[PDB]
Length: 335
Length: 6
Ligand SMILES: *[C@@H]1O[C@H](CO)[C@@H](O[C@@H]2O[C@H](CO)[C@@H](O)[C@H](O)[C@H]2NC(C)=O)[C@H](O)[C@H]1NC(C)=O
Ligand SMILES: *[C@@H]1O[C@H](CO)[C@@H](O[C@@H]2O[C@H](CO)[C@@H](O)[C@H](O)[C@H]2NC(C)=O)[C@H](O)[C@H]1NC(C)=O
Ligand SMILES: *[C@@H]1O[C@H](CO)[C@@H](O)[C@H](O)[C@H]1NC(C)=O
Ligand SMILES: N[C@H](CCC[C@H](N)C(=O)O)C(=O)O
Ligand SMILES: [Fe+3]
Ligand SMILES: [Zn+2]
Ligand SMILES: [Zn+2]
Image 1 (cartoon, rainbow over the protein chains, first blue to last red):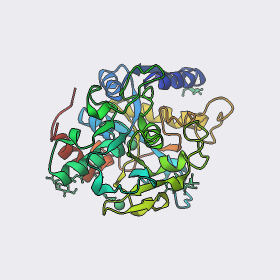
Image 2: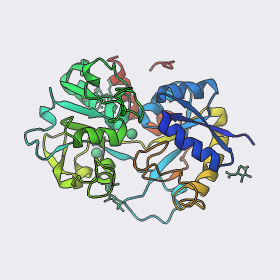
Image 3: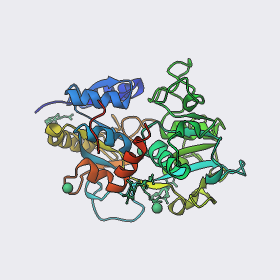
Image 4: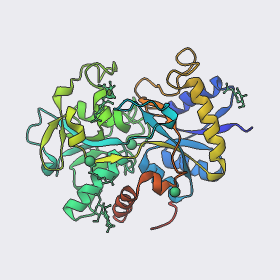
């Protein structure tokens, strides 16, 4: 058999990967790049095998020939007799979150406010809200809608990066990796929690996982869910318990991609590696837990219960869904 | 309806 070379995005992911590689007896080894797009190029060159991706990144990777292999599956809202690996994935809820104290703000008054995004090109943080905004405004100038934003991956001198904070030293402002304080689901929700932005584009789970003591991290440890609201497309505001009826879209779960010629081998190695290090894995928590990273969602989301098999050997457009694909393509016409 | 970004 061959080793699987994973691609880690930024140095925190690389440290986690190196621990996984040590635990796996080098069944998995690590390449690292500074951004997800750069990891996609490593895998296109054959210098890495796979990484797990948000759906917006699966689009980029899929246009370049990489294929979905396994998808993240989080705990299901309904009881299922099926093993996690065979349970159909449910998709996550993209939402717009604000503070309850910021009383005037609705979907219809977002113009000229301060926004917090997971990163350019990601589903809940970017493709869904900016796709909706370009369509409702009839303008491609989405870079001028919010007065200032943190949208990792954008031009660091531009208003889309003006709220980003970089690392402890203030280096790497706006880089689309975990070194940027406001990157990702947790960083964009911390950008709202600290009142750097007025609105954060994240998913429902983020709000729950980082409030009411579900996170012990310093910036989160004291946040209360009741201090947040969701913005609904009909211009109303709801408590965060109401995400099912107040979301922007349902997103396809993050999933692992690879070259087509290495998909089968990546799939077999991951199914064995989660049996060891996955949730209730043989060797988790004693030795190593593949789906933990102290809330930082490194390599996989921390709420992942398993990687699941895909039904119907789907292409990347079947996995993303025709509608989501079309919405991306419409939005990328602006660029 | 278009190609790889890289
Ligand atoms: C919004 O996300 C939260 C967090 O994932 C979901 O709440 C979890 O739901 C699971 C599965 O039902 C429960 O067993 C967990 O205990 C809940 N977590 C917490 C921290 O309360 C919530 O279901 C999601 N809302 C919607 C509409 O999907
Ligand atoms: C933004 O608007 C475009 C243009 O209407 C949307 O594209 C359409 O999507 C629907 C539903 O999937 C399709 O039936 C149409 O065929 C698409 N039209 C075009 C011209 O491609 C797109 O869904 C909207 N974006 C968002 C995020 O809702
Ligand atoms: C390494 O992979 C080989 C071949 O599948 C297997 O025999 C061995 O158990 C694996 N070990 C770990 C620790 O992943
Ligand atoms: N807003 C709708 C569905 C739109 C999903 C579509 N915009 C996509 O591109 O995925 C929802 O509340 O579920
Ligand atoms: Fe996502
Ligand atoms: Zn819906
Ligand atoms: Zn098919």
